[PDB]
Amino acid sequence: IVGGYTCAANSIPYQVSLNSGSHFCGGSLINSQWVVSAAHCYKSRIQVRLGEHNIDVLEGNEQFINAAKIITHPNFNGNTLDNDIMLIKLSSPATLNSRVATVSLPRSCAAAGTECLISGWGNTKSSGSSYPSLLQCLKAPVLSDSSCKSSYPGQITGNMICVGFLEGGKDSCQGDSGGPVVCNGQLQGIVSWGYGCAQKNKPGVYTKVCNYVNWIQQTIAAN
Ligand SMILES: *[B]1(O[C][C][C][N]C([N])=[N+])O[C][C]O1
Ligand SMILES: [Ca+2]
Image (cartoon, rainbow, N blue to C red; front, side, top):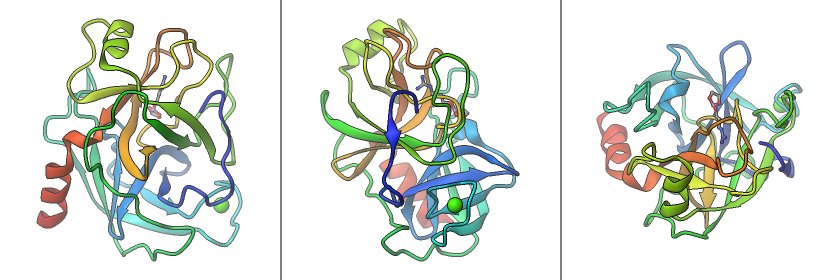
């Protein structure tokens, strides 16, 4: 997250870190047994780390739970990143407490200008790189579909929303992929892509979660 702030410890209790030797992607706890993330984050083995704030220190709230099943959306396009969504079933249920909690799926798609919270452990620099130990947070509005498509002519599918600031300076970045965009207590976005990070007129592009409620419920009932 570039241009954000360090979240209060454990204030984003649905945020997970996906770990394969190190942190490589974010995800969102949506059921005691399931995490939603970005299909482009796929690996065949993943440890899910819940209740993290400092991914470099054991602070006593962590639950480390291996993935038992990893299911990419059947229409995920690895090139365009259309349908950039996957579900991870935990090998044992997360225990839900103040620091490890589910986030709701969308009632409806978020209107333009809806305020959200974006989080993760991705790069904090727009010049160079710095990877944080502490979870970063960013307040950001959903952008109009017109703004989104004007920034990325021909590239925004119906499964993509833009969230952020057309001026630059405030965006998600590499290592945030798969993590949450939460607006009014609902998961509306998954960190997906952007052209570099925090550039002028290149806002962050996020998987449009409100399109996937059927798929997610279907997948949970089937597995
Ligand atoms: B993923 O990259 C996310 C980049 C988001 N960029 C942006 N909002 N301008 O994180 C690790 C793998 O891809
Ligand atoms: Ca920790």
